[PDB]
Image (cartoon, rainbow, N blue to C red; front, side, top):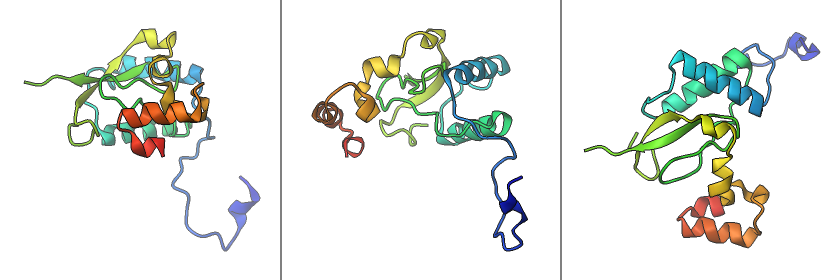
Length: 154
């Protein structure tokens, strides 16, 4: 590897998997969506922050994906994937998870093949994309504050 690896004064050891790192593309997101679907990893599985991390770590291990792609829209309601090509959304379960979610909803993962062609997250919640929202900074602020997302607006 790089010559830094031969530093006798090198401190610690990297906990990063020995895979070449890469950013989640639409292509990779489609492939990983179908892989997870075929393996049965997520369909109808209750959402949790720990399972969110497990998936991030798993995809970095197997495919070197840098784990900053799995962002879903804030909600409440269906939480749409903000990385276009990821075919998995979070769906509120109406009982007759809850402590993780800022809106207090019970959420479950759901496969949606229409997410390969419709960028639902950007269509419905452009304000959650900041400077890439296609809206003025003040309109981003207005829409976020109206939804109660003051931290995101700031």
